Amino acid sequence: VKPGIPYKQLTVGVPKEIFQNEKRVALSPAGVQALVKQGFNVVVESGAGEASKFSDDHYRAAGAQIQGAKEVLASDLVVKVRAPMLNPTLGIHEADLLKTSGTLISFIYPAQNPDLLNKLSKRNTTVLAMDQVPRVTIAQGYDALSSMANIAGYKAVVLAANHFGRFFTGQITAAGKVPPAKILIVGGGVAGLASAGAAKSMGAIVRGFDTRAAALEQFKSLGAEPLEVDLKESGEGQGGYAKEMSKEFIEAEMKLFAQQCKEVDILISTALIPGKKAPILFNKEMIESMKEGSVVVDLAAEAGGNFETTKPGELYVHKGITHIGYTDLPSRMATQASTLYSNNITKLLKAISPDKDNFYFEVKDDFDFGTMGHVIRGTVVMKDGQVIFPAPTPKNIPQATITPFRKTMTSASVYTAGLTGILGLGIAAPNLAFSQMVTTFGLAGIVGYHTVWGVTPALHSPLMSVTNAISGLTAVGGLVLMGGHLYPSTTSQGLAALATFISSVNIAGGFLVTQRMLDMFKRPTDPPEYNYLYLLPAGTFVGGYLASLYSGYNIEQIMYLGSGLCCVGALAGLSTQGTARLGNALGMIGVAGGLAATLGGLKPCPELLAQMSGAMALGGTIGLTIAKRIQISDLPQLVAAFHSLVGLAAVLTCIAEYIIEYPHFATDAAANLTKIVAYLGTYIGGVTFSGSLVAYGKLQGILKSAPLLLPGRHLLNAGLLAASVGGIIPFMMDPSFTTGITCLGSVSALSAVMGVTLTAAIGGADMPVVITVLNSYSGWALCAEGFLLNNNLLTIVGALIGSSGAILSYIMCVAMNRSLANVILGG
Amino acid sequence: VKPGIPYKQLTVGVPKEIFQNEKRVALSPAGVQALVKQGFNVVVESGAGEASKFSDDHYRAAGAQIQGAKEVLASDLVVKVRAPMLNPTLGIHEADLLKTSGTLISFIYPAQNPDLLNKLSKRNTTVLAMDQVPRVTIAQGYDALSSMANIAGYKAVVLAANHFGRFFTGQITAAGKVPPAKILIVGGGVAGLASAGAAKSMGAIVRGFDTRAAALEQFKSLGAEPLEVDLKESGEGQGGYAKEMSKEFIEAEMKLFAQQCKEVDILISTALIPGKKAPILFNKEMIESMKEGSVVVDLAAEAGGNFETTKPGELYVHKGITHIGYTDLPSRMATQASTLYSNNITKLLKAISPDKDNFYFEVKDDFDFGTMGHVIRGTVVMKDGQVIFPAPTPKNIPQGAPVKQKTVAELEAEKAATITPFRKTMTSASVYTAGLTGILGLGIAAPNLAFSQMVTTFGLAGIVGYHTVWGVTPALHSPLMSVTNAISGLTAVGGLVLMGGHLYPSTTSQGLAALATFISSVNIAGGFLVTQRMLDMFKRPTDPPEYNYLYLLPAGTFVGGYLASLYSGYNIEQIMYLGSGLCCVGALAGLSTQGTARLGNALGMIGVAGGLAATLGGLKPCPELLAQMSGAMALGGTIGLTIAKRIQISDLPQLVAAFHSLVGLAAVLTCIAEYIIEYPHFATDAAANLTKIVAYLGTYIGGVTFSGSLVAYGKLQGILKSAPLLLPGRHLLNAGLLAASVGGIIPFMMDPSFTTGITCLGSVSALSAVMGVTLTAAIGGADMPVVITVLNSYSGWALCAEGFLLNNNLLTIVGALIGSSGAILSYIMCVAMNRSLANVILGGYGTTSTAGGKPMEISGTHTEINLDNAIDMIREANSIIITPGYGLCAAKAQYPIADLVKMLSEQGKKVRFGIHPVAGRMPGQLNVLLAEAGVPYDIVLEMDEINHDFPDTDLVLVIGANDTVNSAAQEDPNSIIAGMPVLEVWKSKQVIVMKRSLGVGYAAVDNPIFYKPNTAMLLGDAKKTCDALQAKVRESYQ
Ligand SMILES: NC(=O)c1ccc[n+]([C@@H]2O[C@H](COP(=O)([O-])OP(=O)(O)OC[C@H]3O[C@@H](n4cnc5c(N)ncnc54)[C@H](OP(=O)(O)O)[C@@H]3O)[C@@H](O)[C@H]2O)c1
Ligand SMILES: NC(=O)c1ccc[n+]([C@@H]2O[C@H](COP(=O)([O-])OP(=O)(O)OC[C@H]3O[C@@H](n4cnc5c(N)ncnc54)[C@H](O)[C@@H]3O)[C@@H](O)[C@H]2O)c1
Ligand SMILES: NC(=O)c1ccc[n+]([C@@H]2O[C@H](COP(=O)([O-])OP(=O)(O)OC[C@H]3O[C@@H](n4cnc5c(N)ncnc54)[C@H](O)[C@@H]3O)[C@@H](O)[C@H]2O)c1
């Protein structure tokens, strides 16, 4: 036997209210269907919902039974709204018609009704209180006082108009301004904020006030203008309630209200402190200072009132302003209130006995906070005649490190170190050509910095290919170092032939995979453009050049400027999704013009010309035929596959220079730079080679996605870099061919090891950043090749590619929320 | 003598209303201040305002004169609400108590009341019916039936609740959810739309319905659910009024309403057909099908009804449904009814006699549909005792098809359809092949390698400068120009190279290039002082203290690091030129983020010092010639410092236009100075034809930059006149000057004689100065800032000229940095207005978005208030956006404005500034004036950053601006400034414009923002009005 009594033997009782002009009923038909869902039997008195606009047909259909009056209160559960009284119709008190040990669910206010408690102790019954329910978090779904405060506030707002003779909203008609009404609200609780919301939505403006700090914040939340009192007091008593305030605070607040009273139109006071009367906040000399036609509502007329002038129940128009001072506000919205009050009981009755049919609710003396035993102890006022109204105490709980002088110091430090670096580059100059080349270098660097900045996340990899294609222009270093006859006779010419063979593949394949990374945007609704019109510069620029070689005009430098500006136009126009085709075409024209210019920059032997033509032709054919037969899903896969050659070509070119310039060294002015910069070029190209190989291998499923950690993870890179830097001292001005060539071999092999070590432990989710990083490195190899060869095109193009690739790597780090240091070095 | 009886001996009378349960009164105390400002005398019956809460003290203090009843009715004008009825308190008709041949103002309803018109014809009176006013476009302010319908439609909603049982709004309460209430409307007139507004703002569900097509659209603009029926008969009859329907349409409509009547809770029927009774649209068994507790409100209870169950003056609960069938809804809100009806009678009496004082008011017979004569003929029912109530037909009738509504930005989208993508691609591909032909042409003209290197560094400097100028803050364009006038002082480098001799100059060439150094050393010190005085006005007083003297640390590192590199025997001058060039690029690049501005000034100082020191060390003179150079530069810097610290900031553009002219002189005094000093080399040189052509072109460029700048000075200071001097043929003369200038290179070549070349130099200098004076004075005093900035480009290019001429590498990078800056500023200012550069320079008509003829005309009247409305309306507002113009700083009125804003943001308001790009006499001028007055830079917004906050804005103070707030830029396709991006100030709650009088500044004969009904004028001088606002804010807040 479970501890309780099943729901079939119990019955609830809904009487009508004999109290004066009471219109609401205890249960709606929405609440009669519940508890029949749960299991009770519902007995409803006949004339019960008629003032509440609930006909008896909904009660007969909802599961109840319309019956008399002497037996509705004689039920196991009596659910009223107001506490029982002396019935004048039957001549008997309503407690005398209750049964023995019944259950009553009502408003009680037991501290204000001693004799009702005595008469219910005579009937030896169990009484719960709807008004003693503690306001905790879990019990806010069943709070009768909050619901009645909400409806009373809405009723006061909707009742203020229909007596106020002007608008609340106000509009600029084309007939004159009408200004809005200005409403003041005293006391932000449940009624006041609901009033503020109903008034703010209707069109007026609100300037509410309360002594607490949270209610003012909620006025700011609802859109009100909270008032601030000068005297900085508190507003809290034993929790989040209101205490009786000091007289200095009262006379400051009344001065504030006397200031505000001359300008508002509707004053809705809702001040009420617990356990005492309502605070008087308005004098008769204070309230008569309003305009004629103002409407002034008090909602605390039950326990006194907020005014010196309130007849509780009348609408006497005291000196041209109306007092709305009813004490029964929810009774005028009985169809509304009897819903929410019914919802306040159903959610009570589902919670106190949360099972099939037992109806038990253990009333225990120990309770802490927030637990339902807290609610059960607070709610039950009488248990079997014996009164437990003083509830006990709650248990356990009732709830610039940078100092910005140093910013200016480090900024001035950066600029003064930069100006010293410019001076140090100036001191070590061999001739005028180096100074001129550093000038066009620095300008190309700034041009390359500013020229991306506007790309779209759809367009990271569709431009990288073009940079690949523009970094395919290492082939000029092969073109300025072949010679002899049709076959390459010397080993320097052989290395140059290898370089310009392997670097034609990059050009042809990079532009074709650009063309294939632009076809994957063309939806089948787009207007047919005309790309062949973009051939109109090219024959003008390449072929129109050739007559100048037929007319004896030696045009190479202005051609280099033209190809550099076309490459800038490529990178620029390929950055905003509308002009990507234009950028692709300008990159093609830039490469073609540069290679034709450097081709005419030798006037070679006809067999030598046939050699260079055959080498570039075979390289371009291979670069086409790889890039064409492949999928689409391997296009960003492919770029590193055509990037790995690129720096390798630079390495060969650097080595080629050291082989061609070694007999010229003994009687040389510019002798150190054409070894130091060649050494750095070898380093950069070798790292580019091995790193792009590891990039492709990690993207082609040869290796994993996991960064392969090592024991030596930065000692190892430190040792590689230390040997790499100390590889420049074994040719301190040495006359040996042998130690120079083995230094070149040493830095090449160690650069390969370094690229493997860096690009290995990365992870295939930052590898499209790493492609931009190596594509950024190769531009500096191109600038080194320019310094070796004294060629403006390679200097401009290399600086452009370098700064653009590095800035795109930074923007790709900006797209996600990572840095670059925590990405690369294994943070 | 003028035809009329003046207002002084013309009195009015306001009686108390005598009709049963009438609480309205015809004139408010707010309504008797007009008609007293207009000129009448006002007599009010002693108890007329007591019903609508108007105390008699407000009358007698408003300008009224309290009397009894028999003498208020025998007045020269009687103004009341209803028709004058039989007085019960003494049995006599109120037409008997009228003055003989007087005039009456009320509702009449003459067709329903000819018997009262008999009594009016016996007394030979003139009658103005309020109800018979035809509803035309110039008659919105005086439409009494619309106002009464508006109040009735609101009052029906607010009276339906307090009788309905539950919420309208509905929310998710923790006790449980409640659904919103359903409200049906029948017939969207004016009352139905007001009820729809009142129901939608309270959070309800509105599903109104009407026969006419546009009323359903206005429902769904108000947010209702506009219903429909499955039968298609056109509801409209003769006009905007409806008509009777077919019987079967009535059957289908009552079927639709019987289908939805079982669902809604509130229903308001405003169906009212003119000429006969209101249609019955609901049966009594149809309406008992609703829920128990619904509220049914009928607004047609007087003229029949929309229900067969409506008691015409009472509530009753018929089987659980309340029937609010009140016949006088506006008589319950007598205060608001009296105020609106008073406004209607006020605007009627103001509109009928627009004469100052005659009150003539003639009735005419032939009129156009819509004119005032139409309203006068349709309104006067009895004219001098005889009946003229059947109105004649409106001749010259419009409305064959009245639909244009062609907004401005629609036209350029239509023009975008002409731009077929073949032609887009083709016009893109022509520009690049033109550029590559330009590259090949510049290639062919190369004499050697060094010129090609100079072309390459010129092109890269141009791109660097182009990208770094778009990076600047839009709030710093005016320091920007000043620092360019600093950096353009590097023609001193052009001066010192050709400068030789001893303590004194020896030849004439050495004397020209000492004058060049002298007039260039003004620009350096002057530009850096005026940039320094401008950048520390942007420093807020709460900023961290700025330790700028640390930036002397790089300079002595660089420049002094040069000297020990010169003392030890090196040649770093080509690297010093690069270092100074990068410092000059950084001078604008750091001038981009408002916190590094003084950084970007000190870098300019370091670069100019390094460049001058580098050129000097490369010269290695005797200490006599070094002493001459030091004397020249110190004297020039003395004068440049001592004129930069004397002026005000608002006299800055003159100084800016003064700094260009000196550079335009200096290039001329450096080009000639090389043509003389390079003369014994021309026969034995290959580049000799190069350094002549450049030595031509620079003389042209400075030759235009000089003279025109003096005119651009001379108009802006006021020495020359503000009116553009137009010549009869000035297009032929300017083109002929340009033809002579381009033809002057033909004798300059092919003919190596000394005298014939120097006279070509003098010829091109003279004709270029004439070209500048001719083009400059024909511009106009408004568009003159364009001549400020475009010349700033030319002063750049002159620098580029001598960078090709002296084979120097700093001058090209600096000049390409400056000329790009001038070009981009001129482009921005020719975008901010929709004009083109040829339209500005050559003086065409209007903007580029100008269509053909007939711009639109104004409609409506202008509202003007005083300081007291102004201060109380400032006090109530909680978001103020201020748009100043040039007229603010023309009258020195920014000093009270900054104090006003500092006062109003202590109170807790949100006050900001919105600055149009061309407000002022210089790009970015008004930012500096507002920073001088003391506004922190964080509340000064541009046009693009603030133009979508005008709907969320209480009050906008337009100060001294007309064309930057003109609305016709976005509405009239024929206005003179259509398409110009403006401020959308009319999209807010209330607008104040402060100017002297209702006139124009430069164009736009009338601004249509002055007449929209939430625009208040505050005419007066801005100086006294703004500091009076300062004084009132101080006296009232303290
Ligand atoms: N800023 C530039 O760089 C630049 C460049 C090229 C062209 N523009 C021209 O500049 C124009 C600027 O137009 P905007 O809207 O700023 O001005 P606006 O349209 O020319 O009108 C200025 C207004 O200020 C009023 N005003 C003048 N002095 C006043 C004072 N002491 N107190 C009060 N009000 C005073 C004038 O009223 P009253 O005259 O009736 O007294 C006038 O209505 C543009 O339309 C453009 O055509 C500017
Ligand atoms: N879930 C929960 O437990 C829960 C939820 C919401 C609110 N609450 C509590 O319930 C209360 C909500 O307010 P209510 O309307 O129910 O109570 P209430 O009827 O006591 O409200 C009276 C209002 O008048 C204010 N007031 C009191 N003395 C004043 C004075 N001298 N001057 C000006 N204003 C004065 C009070 O601050 C309050 O805003 C708050 O105390 C809040 O902490 C609890
Ligand atoms: N630009 C203009 O010309 C303009 C602008 C605004 C207003 N106006 C005038 O003001 C008038 C505003 O209307 P009002 O409120 O003064 O007149 P009203 O109160 O008589 O309107 C009656 C309403 O009931 C509707 N109705 C008529 N017969 C019906 C039927 N059988 N069933 C259902 N609905 C029916 C009408 O369409 C109208 O919406 C317009 O009709 C027009 O003449 C004109």
Image: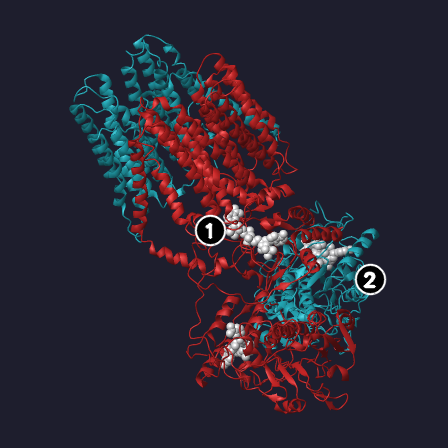
Chain colours: A cyan, B red
Alpha carbon separation for disc pair 2 and 1: 77 Å
What amino acid type is highlighted by mark number 1?
A: Leu
The answer to whether residue B262 of the structure is visible from this angle is: no
Front residue of this view, candidates A277 and A129: A277
Badges 2 and 1: C-beta atoms under 8 Å apart? no
Residue found at the very far top of the displayed protein: A735
* Tag 1 residue: B726
Q: Position of residue B231 (x, y in %)?
A: 41, 78
- Left or right: A258 as drawn, with respect to B192: right
Q: Is mark 1 within 8 Å of ligand 1?
A: no
What amino acid type is highlighted by mark number 2?
A: Asn
Q: Secondary structure at mark 2?
A: loop
In the rendered image, which quarter is residue B447 located in? top left
Front residue of this view, candidates A568 and B261: A568
Q: Residue at x 33, y 31 (%)?
A: A561
- Left or right: B203 as drawn, with respect to A557: right
Q: Position of residue B773 (x, y in %)?
A: 47, 43
Front residue of this view, candidates A823 and B466: B466
Q: Residue at x 38, y 22 (%)?
A: A754
Q: Position of residue A208 (x, y in %)?
A: 70, 57
Q: Position of residue A338 (x, y in %)?
A: 65, 68
Quarter of the figure that contains the N terminus of chain A: bottom right
Neighbourhood count class around disc 2 (C-alpha, 10 Å): few under 14, some 14–19, many 20 upward: some
Q: Is mark 2 within 8 Å of ligand 2?
A: no
* Tag 2 residue: A283
**What chain does badge 1 belong to?**
B
The answer to whether residue B332 is above or below residue A354 is: below
- Left or right: B65 as drawn, with respect to A420: right
Q: Residue at x 58, y 81 (%)?
A: B363
The answer to whether residue B280 is above or below residue A439 is: below
In the rendered image, which quarter is residue A348 located in? bottom right
Q: Secondary structure at mark 1?
A: loop
